[PDB]
Image 1 (cartoon, each protein chain N blue to C red):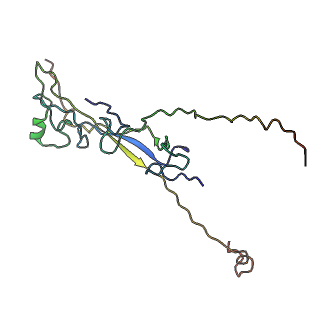
Image 2 (tube, one colour):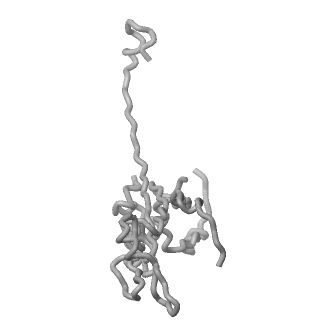
Image 3 (cartoon, rainbow over the protein chains, first blue to last red):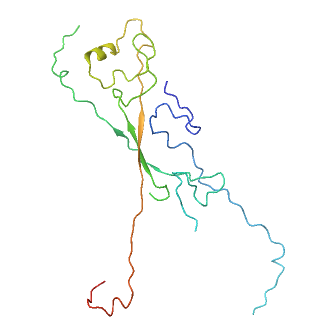
Length: 51
Length: 51
Length: 100
């Protein structure tokens, strides 16, 4: 019946055979989950005297 | 030195730690290698008689 | 291209009449599922083609079903390279002046 058994889970898609398998099996979101700087509450309260 | 190792053969890349791996590990050329029709004699030497 | 691993893979598309078309979906003229389904495949026996011809009747439905297969050709890339050292006094104070 030429199904599309889940290729990620291991079941090869019905069209594929021998050693072919599916190749694009997931859409990569090209936007990373990045963190931000943890805030500072003591560094601002500091005058700088040169040396 | 964080090295690429070999993700295709199983060795995870150094920066890809815990449950992660490279998510573009090859290239689809997207140009299928197909075969043409077999040479056909017999068939073109034929007259037709409509029914 | 860069940033895509080290492997080029393509897709092969086997024709219907081909021994490489080892598919499951196949049902013969008698309406019975068979272990094959690339019709007569690549064999050229008169008896075999006669017995596997997609012959159909007046009131004929699910009678002859074919199947298709797909193949992939992997291709990798490797690295090579050698080198050689050479001392300074092995280039200035030497017989030949064009050793480098």
